[PDB]
Amino acid sequence: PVYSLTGKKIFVAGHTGMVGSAILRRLQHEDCDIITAAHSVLDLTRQGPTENFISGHRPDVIIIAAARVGGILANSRFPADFLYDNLAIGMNLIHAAHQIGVERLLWLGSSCIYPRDAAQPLTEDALLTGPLEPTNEAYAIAKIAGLKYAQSCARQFGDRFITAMPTNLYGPNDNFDPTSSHVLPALIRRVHEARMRGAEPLREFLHVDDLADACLHLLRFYNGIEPVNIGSGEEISIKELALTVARIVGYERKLLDTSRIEALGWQPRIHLEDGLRDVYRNWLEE
Ligand SMILES: NC(=O)c1ccc[n+]([C@@H]2O[C@H](COP(=O)([O-])OP(=O)(O)OC[C@H]3O[C@@H](n4cnc5c(N)ncnc54)[C@H](OP(=O)(O)O)[C@@H]3O)[C@@H](O)[C@H]2O)c1
């Protein structure tokens, strides 16, 4: 263990988010002091307020889960917002963290910022080796710049700042809106509206609580400079996924290379059928 969170002050940026809330849940078990700021009180694109919040509270650990995220329609129609919001968040937090000597910082990348035509399964060193996917290039460029700024701080100063590269997430606080772009929520939705109405390629899905566990694992064990993929491992086809979904509801080429996180002795512990059923019932009861 290169680093222990016990006794440390941990700022979880974006704690109302899907990923941020999972981190906060995993943390309240830990013996630490957790620090949060709602989006309503601290706009993390504002360099002034962000620095004063970091200089006043002085966290040992910053976990950056604050972000502007959305589907293909949002990214192509609001590219300036998707670039600026995410870049300014990362720049303001990384710079403030470097200035006061924050012991550990975690930035969140994304599986969709690798080159569009990079070889599958995606290794972390595929980053920047080719053209970006145009529809979310603005988001990708912001996430890439933040990752590289964290890397430059680790190189120049030895700041222990790392980036995790997740994959498609599901689980608690997912987006079940009818306009959600998340495949699995919409499938549970489309198959449920088909179940009670009585009508006639490979993918990867990672449970948010596994991702949260892996993030704390990287914080406790990972000191490298390069990013680390956090993948599912257990793949499934949209075909096989539909039959898994339909059996849940009673109806009648984008995968990460996880060699690196596996060498750290971490592997996701939630099975797809367990998480889906556990999420199918919460969507009913809510
Ligand atoms: N494919 C992948 O690898 C993948 C998939 C999902 C997530 N991720 C990673 O995880 C990150 C978060 O994803 P999510 O799904 O958790 O996004 P989310 O659910 O939309 O969470 C967004 C969070 O950021 C907060 N926020 C937004 N703008 C802010 C600002 N200006 N100042 C302060 N807080 C602000 C939101 O606050 P309010 O909403 O309360 O304002 C919310 O707390 C993504 O950016 C990405 O790096 C990766």
Image (cartoon, grey):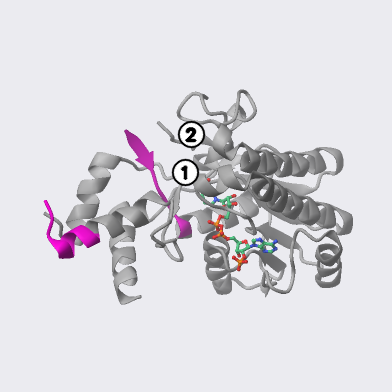
> Which mark is drawn over residue 257?
2
For the point 31% across and 76% down, which residue is it? 285
> Which mark is drawn over residue 158?
none
Q: Is residue 119 left or right of residue 139?
A: left
For the point 76% across and 58% down, which residue is it? 45
Quadrant of the picture in which ligand 1 is shown: bottom right
Q: Nearer the viewer, residue 103 or 263?
A: 103
User: Residue 101: x, y in percent?
Assistant: 85, 56
Q: Is residue 30 left or right of residue 148?
A: left
Q: Which residues are magenta?
A: 192-208
For the point 64% across and 48% down, which residue is it? 82
Quadrant, the C terminus? bottom left
Q: How many marks?
A: 2
Q: Is residue 188 on the magenta stretch?
A: no
User: Residue 260: x, y in percent?
Assistant: 54, 37
Q: Of all residues shown, which one is farthest toward the front?
A: 77
Q: Nearer the viewer, residue 28 or 285?
A: 285
Q: Is residue 100 left or right of residue 37?
A: right
The quarter of the picture where residue 273 lies is bottom left
Q: Nearer the viewer, residue 226 or 93?
A: 93
Q: Give the residue type at disc 2.
A: Asp
- Decide if residue 49 is in sight here: yes
Does the residue tagged 2 have its C-beta within 8 Å of any atom of ligand 1? no
- Decide if residue 265 is in sight here: no
Q: Kindly identify which residue carries mark 1.
A: 231
For the point 58% across and 63% down, which residue is it? 20
Task: Specify which label sits upstream in the sequence, 2 or 1.
Answer: 1
